[PDB]
Amino acid sequence: TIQPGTGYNNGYFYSYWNDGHGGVTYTNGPGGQFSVNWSNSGNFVGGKGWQPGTKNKVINFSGSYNPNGNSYLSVYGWSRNPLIEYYIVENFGTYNPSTGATKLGEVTSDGSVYDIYRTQRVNQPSIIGTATFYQYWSVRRNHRSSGSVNTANHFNAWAQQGLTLGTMDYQIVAVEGYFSSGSASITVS
Image (cartoon, rainbow, N blue to C red; front, side, top):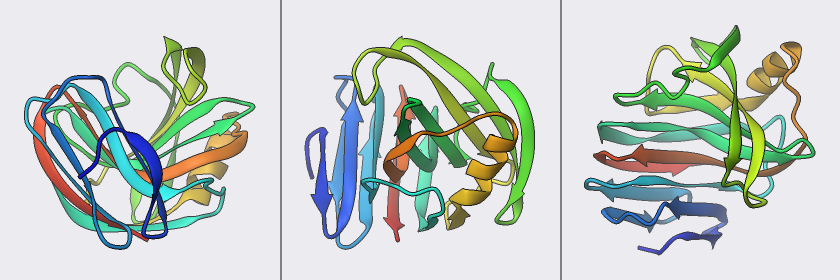
């Protein structure tokens, strides 16, 4: 069980961030495993993966995901020049993270159709500090908490829609929560 921060554990990069509100317990386990239990948390994001990620990685994940409110499970990462925060959402709770976003297309990957969106974060926290940047989203229609994600299918679909990515920074499978409660245990590979 660790405090917010980044590092490496058992061969995998990890990132755990929160907004200062308590109620979140993030734990790194063997191999690519991590678990999170939260009770009336604020906003938090935590998970395991790689630093840096790649544009053709096939990410495997499996586990249990039980959100009680706003939350989502997905492949999460960043690129620089351009600065982009992206998500390939595999499951979520009460709130579809693409709400209010601009739909640009669709892609069929790993057994399901995903809706593609682009949104803009204005003067918000980022891997390089306060900044304005775009967010790319692929939201799976058929929710699941286990499977394989061929990231190239999404990155190429985004590119076809004019959404380009820069040089990759981290790439993880993360559990996010936003003023809710829940529990999750995920193993990445």
